[PDB]
Structure formats: structure tokens, C-alpha cells
């Protein structure tokens, strides 16, 4: 098994070039958390006209006809249990996505949480530590395509 995947996850860098977040190609668009102020490290994507959505901390542009194929697929059905992401396992219970304490931080905004069939279930924005875990502030869409944002008490944007 070789992890040969399309180009869908992109870095957003700050003025001196530090990775401060992530952008993703999904459902025909390139989206990135609005709070992440930097540039998408991509010669084509960085020149697109992005549309702001402050109510959801989202910013998006339309995928160039070509790249439209190189993208993730979303899914609004997330039964409780475990999910995957860059750092390992993400748990979903009580309507909340949690990871262990001390794992999330700067650079993790824009990162997707996915299921075993490789579909995106959510996009990470920040986290609020509660006891031995961290409750994630994520963006998700429902069955009727409505964007939804969940933000725990005391959430700190990553």
C-alpha cells in the first residue's frame, strides 16, 4: 500500500512563510478558515477570487475546471465512534469531536476529519480543552447542504 493521493490539501503560510493553517479542495471549491491570515502556497489557487463567509469562519473560491476532479467528497452522516485525521484518531460522541489534550494547535486549522471510506466529515477550526481531552470547533454541513458551525465554550482558534 502506497499513499498516492491527488492534490487536495494545501498549506497557508504567514508573511515570513510559517505554516499557519490549511486549505482544501472539496465539492468543487477551495476552502480555508477565514481567521487564518496568510497565502495559499499554490501558484494557481493563490490567485483566485475568494468569497468570505464570516458567520461560519469560511473563505472559498471555485475550483479550476481541471482540479475539480482532484478533490474530497463530503458526507453529512457521522455515526458516533472513531474518525481519522493527521494526528491519529478523532472521537465523535455527544455531538462533539474530541482529540487528546496537547495534540492540536497552530497549523491544524483547515485540516479535515475523515471516515474510513475517505470522506470528509468535518473541518477543524480550533479547540477548547476540557479535562483530559480537547473539544473541537469544526464546520460541517447537514443533509440539506446547510453549513453549520459548532464552537465549544472557550474555544481557541488554531
Image (tube, helix red, strand yellow):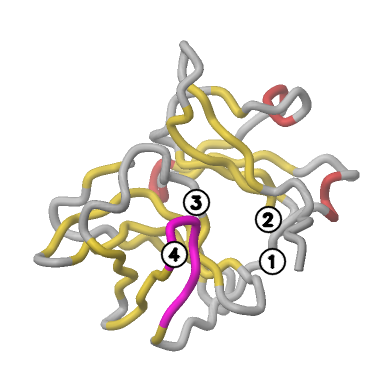
Q: Residues within 10 Å of mark 2 (few under 14, many from 20)?
A: many
Q: Position of residue 119 (x, y in %)?
A: 63, 71
Q: Residue at x 47, y 11 (%)?
A: 16
Q: Earlier in the sequence, mark 4 or mark 1?
A: 1
- Picture coordinates of residue 130, whole percent (x, y): 12, 63
Going 88% across and 44% down the picture, which residue do you hit? 65
Badge number at residue 59: none
Q: Is the residue marked by circle 1 packed among few (<14), some (14-19), or many (20+) residues within 10 Å? A: few
Q: Which residue is mark 4?
A: 88
Query: CB under 8 Å between callouts 2 and 1?
Result: yes
Q: Is residue 81 left or right of residue 26?
A: left
Viewer-proximal residue among 86 and 64? 86
Marks 4/1: CA–CA distance: 20 Å
Q: Which residue is mark 2?
A: 26
Q: Give the residues in magenta.
A: 82-88
Which one is closest to the eye, mark 4 or mark 3?
4
* Residue indicated by mark 3: 111
Label 2 residue SS = strand
Spatial CA distance of label 2 from label 1 is 6 Å
The residue labelled by disc 1 is 73
- How many marks do you count on the picture? 4
Amino acid at each position: 500500500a502506497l499513499k498516492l493521493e491527488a492534490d487536495r490539501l494545501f498549506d497557508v503560510k504567514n508573511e515570513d512563510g510559517d505554516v499557519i493553517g490549511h486549505a482544501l479542495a472539496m465539492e468543487g471549491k477551495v476552502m480555508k478558515p477565514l481567521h487564518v491570515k496568510g497565502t495559499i502556497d499554490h501558484p494557481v489557487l493563490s490567485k483566485l477570487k475568494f468569497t468570505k463567509s464570516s458567520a461560519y469562519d469560511m473563505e472559498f473560491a471555485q475550483l479550476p475546471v481541471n482540479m475539480r476532479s482532484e478533490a474530497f467528497t463530503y458526507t453529512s452522516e457521522h455515526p458516533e465512534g472513531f474518525y481519522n485525521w493527521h494526528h491519529g484518531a478523532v472521537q465523535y460522541s455527544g455531538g462533539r469531536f474530541t482529540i487528546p489534550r496537547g495534540v492540536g494547535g497552530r497549523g491544524d486549522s483547515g485540516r479535515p476529519i475523515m471516515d474510513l471510506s475517505g470522506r470528509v466529515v468535518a473541518i477543524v477550526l480550533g479547540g477548547a480543552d476540557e479535562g483530559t481531552r480537547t473539544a473541537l470547533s469544526v464546520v460541517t454541513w447537514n443533509s440539506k447542504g446547510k453549513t453549520i458551525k459548532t464552537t465549544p465554550e472557550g474555544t481557541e482558534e488554531w
